[PDB]
Length: 246
Ligand SMILES: NS(=O)(=O)c1cccc(Nc2ncc3ccc4sc(-c5ccccc5)cc4c3n2)c1
Image (cartoon, rainbow, N blue to C red):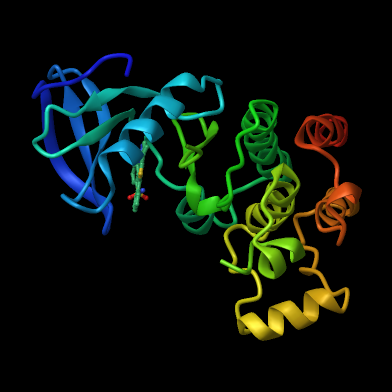
């Protein structure tokens, strides 16, 4: 539980919600800007919160959002993360649409891939890798969050709820699509059924204009019907890294 926080927290304004709790922009010790995630009483068992926080504090990577600590003396319970200045990647891409060079967008994908490669190696399955679950820090660094939606699901996921790092990769491909379309909604005008049919028939998200043919190729490797046919994040990372240089 590396560092338990009492009330050295200043709650400034809330920024999120949804039974689980509320999210607040705050300050710890009147100095460090933080995002405080509080949990609604009786919205999560205590051992789930406890075992979850320990996992997130055991994980450490430059591309994974860091935790300052947790509050559990009850008041209610909460998690204290470092504050990511520019919010969620989805919102960021949308409001900044038209101001991105392709290199920038590719750089964003590489950030996410590094954090994902790290989690992969740590045998951690994300299960909800989407641009909305990624955060933008100052200088456009992207960090994966919420690491500890059939539009992002691989076939074995909407069929067997069979999660793995390989299903995460598929999700990463869709995230790549979100990044290059500059925040567009994938399969915006299609129901679950239509998405499942289209995907099952071999259709894939169209190539965004900012996505080079080489970037799109990688996106399609992530969307290979067979998990074993998709590259592991460790491999993807180097593929993206080479393309980035041109
Ligand atoms: N998430 S947001 O409201 O777009 C936003 C705006 C401006 C700055 C941030 N920064 C930040 N930094 C570190 C974080 C680390 C934890 C969480 S959980 C969360 C959330 C959850 C459930 C619904 C809505 C938001 C945002 C953040 C978080 N957020 C977030």
